[PDB]
């Protein structure tokens, strides 16, 4: 339920300056 | 056990695709603002004279310029357009690998 | 530059992945799919009219005419045999695309058209300036390990290469060829002395400023035919007109070089032409100034157009985009849902994405309803039929 | 932890590949999704093929037919096959459109659009400008006349999970497709994004989809097997014809075309379809040298050398005797005689093949002693012995 | 007694990021006079290039990686393309694949996969730069022609090695090869024979397009000499000191010996000879670990060897009866790893030892 | 004394090693000098630093740290292109027949050379008789090994019992023993001894040692054929041969390996190893020609494939010496034999290919389709005993790869170090082939036969459970 599928998949490939902040750059690593 | 299939993608191509994806995302805001299936283009309006104004979108050579009045220019600050509705000839420049003639070569027929 | 090579490598990887996805989705799109990798690539493919139906077996035997494109070895004129599953069944019946004959040929064959009145006589376009008329009945099945034998007829009236070749369906003989010397010649043949070596061209047609890329006879009238060149013009020639330089019609018909041409089997007026402008156009001979619908769904040049032999409003095109599309003329211009509009125009009926290199040639089987055989440049031949669900 | 980084990389490689394909296939598709049996929900249109094609022209005719600044004109022509890009002519079917460019700091304006509409309305143009609003004068010219919630759980080693919820029902997260039925969505997920395994498990509240990496996933090169081992700079040349071993495949023959069923989620080949290697050097085998030259012979050179060395390593033997034994062993090994009745012909072949070597070595007495010994060992005959002796004498006379 | 006359002092110390043991170091001896001293390092999945300046300044130039597989590099060799004078570096290990890297272009030029197991050494012919000799774990050694990408000969078989070949070395003029292995043997393969010369010529005169048959590689089954009575265990490394042989094993010594009797010439030695004479042994301590190669400079004046604790012995070979004396030992209080290999510059002025802690140590001659 | 001599020897050795070191140093100096002179040419291009590549923005970085002061440097890593590998296998040697593995002083100068004395036939042919194996027509063969148990390797065995000869008229020429009066009678009397005439004095002809040995060997071979002896020996006219002969006269589970039986004056019945070990008394053994235990040949018209043929019924290839009508004997040099029970003997094997298997490691793929029950290949290897087999298996168990193949009660075929291409066949619970040991010419050989019809390019399997070694232990 936390985050969304599209947000998680958008936090998987880009992990650099263009991370778009939001919940994608949030604490997705380490749960 | 069985011999390794030796996937054809390898890691050099994966690195190239990752770099291209980062550049495209930062350029077009496809993932964040485009909802994953649309491209967001920003216009540029400075001054307009009434006898109409021409606006150029930030992604070059993708959408042709148009003439609009002051109110239309104000209301047209941002534009979102599906990738299916993009012009077919001009959508190929968004990525060199969107479509490329692999055997460019010569001769043939 | 290294950028070009890197992009080529990435594109090759993407092509492989797309092919894997298509093969994974194959059974949900077709009713039959058979793929055979030839020893050498073939630049031509045409079904023979004859069909053999054995009694008590659930399959039939059809024939094919193929060429060969070898880098340094001997070139042949291979005639293959294909076994189609009829309506019932097969899983394992041993050979299914086995060859039948090989005849030695001097150079690769660009066209392998057969004579409609007598399918035994086969005419081919050689890379040289001579067009050879073969007769595969007389020649032995096993090729002789020597040079090119007697072709039994050597028609020579050209001065360079060629790619266009047509046979008169209404009259016996009367072959037409379009070559790269800006000329098209007419050969009477048939009424020629036996043990002949060289046959002179009956008539010489010169009205195109550029290389003529195709030529075709009219399927209903025995005295009229049309030719297309790469200078963006479609001419409609008339035989026995006492004028070999000025054609009856000179419609420009396209923006870029025009490649192919095909007449409608049923209608006496409708024809279609293809070009490098990524566009296929339909016309009616009664009104040549007005152009009918124009299909725009390809991404590269279109090299072939073929009207369906059994349907009024079905037509297919192929090209360098590694794709083949099927068009329906009765479906053009009607309302569609947004999802369908995103998928494609309503006229587009099918997109076949099973090939990895450029499509070289294809044809429909006269003896079977909706089956097409296509050959690509990576030495791969495919015989396929779309699902009956698509066309009800 | 390194485990989380490994999991992220493992799920990020296929995700990146499929995101690239999702971007690419919205412009250049491989096949239409309205032609799939499980996705036939789209294209809800029937067939009306009951009209002649001879009325198309009549219908069309009835419906439609019935400081200092330099001024230079820019004309762009349509791109032919020979030309890589569209030619542009700067004038201080042939022509696509006309444009005006000012160079002094640059500004390009167009008069005619693609449809040749009455464009270029009078007024200021806020077009992009590149050096080499503003207070100074501007160069602007106008040409005119005056429900069903779905959950995802990414599993790693059946121990690590990532709770997630889909924002759009019946929407593929990767391809952003719209499969409005759940069964169609599951089938599309299984068939298109086959690098994962989608084990739908159902939930008391909604429906849960468990995604895990695919262990096997045979995704090797599907083209010519020889290209996978070529040296860099020549692999995948794609420049000309290449010979290959014929092979036949049958992907679909006659599908059963079953209906929709939720019980699911609760080929033939012939010929050489492999790359073969040499037994000796373990190098790839080209088809041009595969049918013949089976590379297996009766007498290997190592065996010949070993036999020669072992014969010459004896202590109690004469030089000519050792030479004759080595010659006989080499001849027998090369020709593979297996029969006592064949020994008679073997003797004649030995005297007719190695006669020059025997004459040069001057071991005729040793050879005749060997013949006598072999006769005493049964086989051969006195007629064979004296025939061979006279043949050797005649050869000696012919030589001298 | 005296600790020679060369004094070496540590001036710099690096540390690779991958933290994995490094197995090879090679100085580029083909560089012209006055050019910067460039050396290459291999270890784990990466190969790195460094350049030496004055006052102990070493600058990292280039770095590579093989992330597609589980490669574990073990060795390196420097060559050059005489057609364009571009230097080349060849690496191998673990996977049994040889990669020839072009540092100027920063790309992998060629690849060779015909071995059956991991490769432990690569060497180049002193006279012909296109011939590479690889010793592998499949009890065989192969000679390649990297110019035409053909396999010239294979050096195993009926009378070859019975176990992994660990090391090999050419002669001074490149006429004989001596091989060491884990089967206690030291075989001397001779490449001066007419068969080998004809094989090399045929390899240089081969065109794959004109012929349909493949190349006929020579399969040498019988060595020209073989001795098992010098070492009681596996031989870690071998080297040619002119016409004598320096070999090392787990016995904590490097014995200098010659084939044949005391006055037997090396050239006139029969394959059936079984006489070996030793001359001297160099003594060190705490080197019971295996896979630790020693080194010698271009002029064969000095030789150096690592240690499993961190010491570095340098022997002077110009002294009469070099087997005596105790040499010069170099130690630093911050070194505690195992020196896998060392290297000398073309001029014997800079010596660099590579430890197993992914660290690089530099010693300079005060002179 | 001894100590002084030892000290002198040690000092001399010290000077010798010093001189050797000096000479080696001089050679090293010369070679290094010429090498440096050769290197003095050429230019060689220097290398440059690697910067950030725009082709990969998300590229990795490599940082090195200097312990002794100095800053830290960071650079981007380049990526190497992928390469395809092959399965791991060790070197082996080709083989076509089995290879047995086991772990002048006699004063006989060459008679062809000038230096050759006179010796008896028992010593002039001892080497030829000892070092010849009649089972394979090779001198010191690799398959059959002798343990020196037999007396001089059975010289000529005892088959040369055909001593009966008949005199014929029409002499070869003017010079003969028959022409001289009394010579024939004297020769008959001399040969009649078993267990006066010809008073003409012998001719004064020199007889060297080599000539005497030649004449003795020829006499032993040809009995009393004096004219033929004179014709065979260089010069040595009939009268001289007769004179030499006159001068020399007076004055002075249940399968056991087959081993030939050479019992004299005893019927082959419950006494020789052929009878004892229950195996047929073959041709190579020296029993009587009418031995009861000898296996009669088959009289088939052709084929010899069906069970009607006794040779196939007894699991045995048709011997060329016995089977004449079935076509095995005919066309020995040629091919296309009508009899099908001769494949192993003729060595006609199918074409095989090598490629990585779909199960593990390497595998064998058949080039062309094969019908049912057809010969494919033979399992060649090295013949070792059972104890050696166990020792080799213990050695090879370290890396889990066994190529052993049981053959008989005391022999094993090991294709590890040397073998054929058929060794790359994988075990399967549904094999496509099977193995049968067929007694070909007295030697047990393994033949691999197709169990069912096999398509083109099909991978080859056969069941490994029949072998003595545990198949599941290795794979
Ligand atoms: Zn033998
Ligand atoms: Zn017996
Ligand atoms: Zn007996
Ligand atoms: Zn008997
Ligand atoms: Zn029989
Ligand atoms: Zn028989
Ligand atoms: Zn028989």
Image: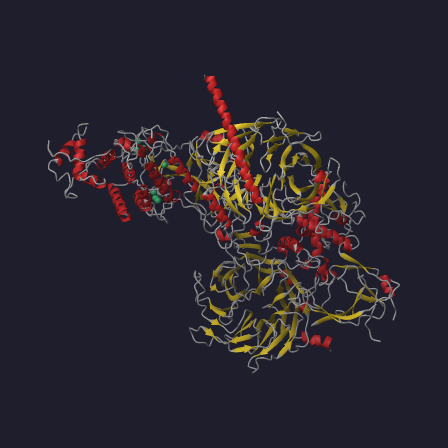
Q: Can residue C54 be seen?
A: no
Color theme of the render: secondary structure
- D109 w.r.t. F166: above or below: below
Q: Can residue D308 be seen?
A: yes
Assign ligand 4 to one image quadrant.
top left
Percent position (x, y) of residue F467?
47, 35
- D242 w.r.t. F97: above or below: below
Closer to the camera in the image, F447 or E207:
E207
Percent position (x, y) of residue E84?
60, 51
Q: Residue furthest right?
A: D135
- In this rendering, would D233 be left or right of F200? right
Q: Residue furthest top?
A: F1
Q: Residue furthest bottom?
A: C242
Q: Quadrant of residue F29?
A: top right
- In this rendering, would C43 be left or right of B64? left
Closer to the camera in the image, F243 or F122:
F243
Which quadrant is the C terminus of chain F positioned in?
Answer: top right
Closer to the camera in the image, F18 or D392:
F18
- In this rendering, would F99 be left or right of B51? left
Which quadrant is the N terminus of chain F positioned in?
Answer: top left
Q: Quadrant of residue B86?
A: bottom right
Q: How many marks?
A: 0
Closer to the camera in the image, F172 or C198:
F172
Percent position (x, y) of residue C99?
49, 59
Percent position (x, y) of residue C229?
61, 72
């Amino acid at each position: 339920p936390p985050a969304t599928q599209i947000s998680d998949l958008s936090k998987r490939k880009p992990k650099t300056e263009d991370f778009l902040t939001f919940l994608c750059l949030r604490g997705s690593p380490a749960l | 056990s069985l011999p390794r299939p030796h996937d054809f993608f390898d890691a050099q191509t994966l690195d190239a695709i990752r770099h291209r994806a980062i550049c495209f995302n930062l350029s077009a805001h496809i993932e964040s603002l485009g909802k994953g299936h649309s491209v967001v283009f920003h216009s540029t309006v400075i001054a307009k004279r009434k006898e109409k104004l021409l606006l150029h979108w930030m992604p070059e050579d993708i959408l042709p310029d148009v003439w609009v009045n002051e109110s239309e220019r104000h209301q047209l600050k941002t534009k979102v357009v599906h990738l299916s509705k993009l012009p077919k000839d001009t959508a190929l420049l968004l990525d060199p690998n969107i479509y490329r003639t692999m055997p460019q070569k010569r001769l043939k027929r | 530059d290294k950028e070009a090579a890197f992009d080529d490598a990435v594109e090759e990887r993407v092509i492989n992945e797309e092919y894997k996805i298509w093969k994974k989705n194959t059974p949900f799109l077709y009713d039959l799919v058979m793929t055979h990798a030839l020893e050498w690539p073939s630049l031509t493919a045409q079904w023979l009219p004859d069909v053999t139906r054995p009694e008590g077996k659930d399959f039939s035997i059809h024939r094919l005419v193929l060429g060969t494109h070898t880098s340094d070895e001997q070139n042949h004129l291979v005639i293959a045999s294909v076994q189609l599953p009829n309506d019932d069944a097969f899983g394992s019946v041993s050979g299914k695309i086995e060859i039948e004959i090989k005849i030695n040929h001097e150079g690769e064959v660009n066209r392998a058209r057969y004579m409609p009145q007598n399918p035994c006589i086969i005419a081919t376009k050689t890379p040289s300036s001579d067009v050879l008329v073969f007769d595969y009945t007389k020649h032995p099945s096993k090729p002789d390990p020597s040079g090119e034998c007697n072709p039994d007829l050597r028609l020579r009236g050209h001065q360079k290469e060629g790619y266009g070749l047509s046979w008169n369906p209404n009259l016996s003989g009367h072959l037409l060829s379009a070559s790269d010397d800006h000329t098209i010649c007419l050969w009477d043949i048939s009424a020629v002395p036996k043990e002949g070596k060289v046959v002179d061209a009956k008539t010489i047609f010169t009205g195109h400023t550029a290389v003529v890329e195709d030529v075709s006879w009219h399927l209903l009238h025995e005295s009229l035919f049309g030719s297309v060149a790469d200078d963006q013009k479609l001419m409609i020639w008339d035989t026995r007109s006492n004028n070999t330089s000025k054609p009856s019609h000179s419609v420009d018909a396209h923006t870029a070089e025009v490649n192919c041409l095909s007449f409608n089997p049923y209608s006496e007026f409708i024809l279609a032409t293809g070009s490098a402008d990524k566009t296929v156009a339909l016309w009616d001979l009664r009104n040549l100034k007005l152009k009918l619908h124009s299909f725009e769904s390809h991404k590269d040049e279109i090299f072939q157009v073929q009207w369906s032999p059994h349907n009024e409003t079905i037509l297919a095109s192929s090209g360098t985009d590694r794709r083949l599309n099927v068009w329906d003329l009765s479906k053009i211009g009607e309302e569609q849902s947004p999802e369908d509009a995103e998928d494609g125009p309503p006229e587009l009926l099918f997109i076949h994405g099973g090939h990895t290199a450029k499509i070289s040639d294809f044809s429909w089987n006269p003896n079977e309803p909706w089956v097409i055989c296509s050959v690509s440049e990576d030495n791969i031949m495919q015989v396929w039929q779309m699902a009956e669900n698509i066309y009800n | 932890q390194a485990d989380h980084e490994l999991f992220l990389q493992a799920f990020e490689k296929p995700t990146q590949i499929y995101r690239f394909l999702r971007t690419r296939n919205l412009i250049a598709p491989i096949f239409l999704h309205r032609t799939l049996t499980y996705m036939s929900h789209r294209n809800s249109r029937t067939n009306i093929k009951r009209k002649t094609f001879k009325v198309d022209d009549m219908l069309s005719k009835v419906e439609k037919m019935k400081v200092t600044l330099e001024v230079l004109l820019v004309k762009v022509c349509h791109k032919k096959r020979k030309d890589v890009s569209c030619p542009i002519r700067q004038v201080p079917h042939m022509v696509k459109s006309y444009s005006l460019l000012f160079r002094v700091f640059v500004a390009q304006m167009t008069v005619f659009d693609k449809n040749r509409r009455l464009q270029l309305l009078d007024g200021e143009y806020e077009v992009a400008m590149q050096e080499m609003f503003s207070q100074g004068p501007t160069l602007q010219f106008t040409l005119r006349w005056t429900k069903l919630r779905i959950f995802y759980q990414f599993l790693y080693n059946n121990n690590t999970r990532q709770q997630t919820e889909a924002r759009d029902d019946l929407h593929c997260p990767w391809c952003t497709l719209n499969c409005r039925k759940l069964y169609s969505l599951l089938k599309h997920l299984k068939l298109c994004h086959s690098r994962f395994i989608f084990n739908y498990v159902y939930h008391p509240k909604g429906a849960r989809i468990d995604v895990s990496i695919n262990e096997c996933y045979d995704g090797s090169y599907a083209g010519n097997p020889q290209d996978i081992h070529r040296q860099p700079g020549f692999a995948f040349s794609r420049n000309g014809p290449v010979k290959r071993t014929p092979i036949t495949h049958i992907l679909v023959c006659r599908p059963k075309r079953t209906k929709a069923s939720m019980s699911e989620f609760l080929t033939y080949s012939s010929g050489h379809n492999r790359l073969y290697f040499h037994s000796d050097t373990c190098l790839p085998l080209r088809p041009q040298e595969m049918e013949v030259d089976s590379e297996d012979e009766k007498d290997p050179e190592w065996l010949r050398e070993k036999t020669i060395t072992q014969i010459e390593e004896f202590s109690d033997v004469n030089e000519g005797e050792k030479e004759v034994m080595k010659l006989w062993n080499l001849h027998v090994m090369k020709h593979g005689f297996i029969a006592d009745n064949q020994m008679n012909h073997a003797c004649m072949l030995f005297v007719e093949n190695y006669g020059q070597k025997i004459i040069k070595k001057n071991l005729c007495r040793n050879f005749m002693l060997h013949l006598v010994s072999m006769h005493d060992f049964n086989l051969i005959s006195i007629m064979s012995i004296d025939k061979a002796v006279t043949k050797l004498r005649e050869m000696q006379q012919k030589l001298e | 007694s005296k600790k020679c006359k060369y004094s070496f002092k540590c001036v710099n110390s690096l540390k690779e990021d991958h933290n994995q043991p490094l197995f090879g170091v090679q100085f580029n001896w083909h560089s012209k006079e006055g050019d910067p001293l460039v050396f290459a390092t291999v270890g784990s999945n990466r190969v790195t290039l460094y350049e030496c300046h004055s006052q102990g300044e070493i600058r990292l130039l280039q770095s590579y990686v093989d992330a597609d597989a589980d490669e574990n590099f073990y060795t390196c060799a420097w060559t050059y393309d005489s057609n364009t004078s571009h230097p080349l570096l060849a690496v191998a290990g673990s996977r049994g694949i040889i990669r020839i890297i072009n540092p100027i272009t920063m790309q992998c030029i060629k690849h060779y996969v015909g071995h059956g197991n991991a490769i432990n050494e690569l060497k180049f012919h002193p006279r012909d730069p296109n011939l590479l000799l690889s010793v592998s774990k499949d009890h065989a050694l192969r000679l390649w022609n990297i110019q035409t990408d053909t396999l010239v000969a294979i050096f195993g078989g009926v009378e070859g090695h019975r176990d992994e070949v660990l090391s090999a070395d050419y002669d001074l003029l490149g006429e004989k090869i001596m091989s060491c292995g884990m089967d206690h043997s030291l075989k001397l393969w001779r490449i001066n024979s007419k068969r080998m010369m004809n094989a090399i010529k045929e390899s240089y005169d081969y065109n794959p397009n004109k012929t349909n048959r493949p190349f006929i590689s020579q399969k040498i089954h019988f060595p020209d000499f073989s001795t098992r009575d010098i070492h009681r265990n596996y031989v870690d490394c071998v080297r040619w000191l002119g016409d004598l042989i320096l070999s090392k094993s787990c016995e904590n010594a490097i014995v200098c010996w010659k084939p044949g009797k005391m006055e037997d010439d090396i050239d006139k030695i029969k394959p059936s000879e079984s006489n070996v004479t030793i001359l001297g042994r160099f003594d060190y301590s705490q080197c019971d670990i295996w896979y630790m190669r020693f080194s010698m400079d271009f002029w064969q004046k000095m030789l150096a060897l690592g240690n499993q604790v961190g010491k570095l012995y340098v022997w002077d070979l110009e002294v009469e009866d070099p087997h005596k004396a105790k040499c010069t030992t170099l130690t630093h209080h911050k070194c505690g790893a195992a020196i896998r290999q060392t290297s000398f510059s073309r001029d014997s002025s800079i010596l660099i030892a590579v430890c197993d802690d992914a660290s690089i140590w530099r010693w300079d001659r005060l002179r | 004394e001894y100590m002084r001599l030892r000290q002198l020897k040690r000092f001399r050795r010290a000077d010798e090693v010093k001189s050797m070191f000096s000479s080696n140093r001089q050679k090293i100096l010369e070679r290094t000098e010429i090498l440096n002179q050769e290197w003095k040419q050429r230019r060689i291009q220097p290398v440059h630093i690697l910067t950030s590549v725009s082709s990969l923005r998300g590229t990795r970085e490599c940082s090195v740290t200097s312990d002794l002061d100095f800053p830290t440097q960071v650079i981007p890593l380049k990526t190497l292109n992928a390469v395809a590998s092959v399965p791991i296998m060790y070197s082996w040697s080709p083989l076509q027949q089995n290879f047995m593995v086991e772990d002048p002083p006699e004063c006989t100068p060459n008679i062809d050379g000038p230096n050759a004395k006179s010796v008896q036939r028992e010593q002039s042919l001892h080497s030829f008789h000892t070092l010849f194996c009649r089972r394979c027509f090779k001198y010191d063969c690799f398959l059959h090994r002798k343990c020196n148990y037999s007396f001089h390797a059975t010289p000529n065995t005892y088959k040369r019992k055909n001593t009966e000869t008949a005199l014929d008229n029409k002499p070869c020429g003017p010079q003969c023993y028959q022409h001289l009066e009394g010579a024939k009678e004297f020769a008959a009397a001399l040969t009649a001894e078993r267990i006066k005439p010809n008073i003409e004095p012998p001719e004064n002809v020199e007889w060297s040692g080599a000539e005497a040995s030649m004449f003795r060997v020829l006499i032993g071979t040809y009995y009393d054929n004096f004219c033929a002896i004179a014709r065979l020996i260089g010069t040595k006219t009939c009268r001289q041969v007769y004179e030499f002969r006159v001068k020399e006269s007076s004055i002075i589970n249940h399968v056991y390996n087959y081993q030939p039986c050479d019992h004299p004056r005893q019927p082959c019945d419950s006494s020789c190893p052929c009878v004892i070990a229950q195996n047929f008394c073959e041709k190579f053994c020296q029993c009587s020609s009418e031995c009861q235990n000898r296996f009669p040949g088959c009289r088939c018209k052709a084929q010899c494939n069906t069970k009607q043929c006794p040779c196939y019924l007894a699991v045995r290839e048709c011997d060329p010496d016995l089977c004449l009508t079935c076509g095995a004997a005919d066309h020995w040099d040629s091919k296309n034999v009508s009899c099908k029970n001769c494949s192993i003997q003729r060595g006609s094997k199918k074409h095989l290919l090598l490629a990585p298997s779909d199960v593990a490691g390497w595998g064998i793929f058949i080039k062309d389709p094969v019908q049912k029950n057809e010969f494919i290949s033979e399992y060649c290897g090295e013949i070792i005993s059972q104890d050696e087999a166990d020792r080799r298996g213990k050695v090879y168990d370290k890396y889990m790869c066994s190529f052993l193949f049981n053959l008989n009660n005391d022999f094993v075929v090991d294709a590890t170090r040397k073998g054929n291409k058929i060794r790359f066949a994988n075990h399967s619970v549904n094999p496509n082939c099977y193995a049968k040991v067929m007694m070909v010419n007295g030697d047990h050989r393994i033949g691999i036969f197709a169990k069912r019809a096999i398509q083109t390019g099909e991978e080859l399997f056969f069941d490994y459970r029949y072998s003595q070694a545990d198949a599941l232990k290795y794979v």
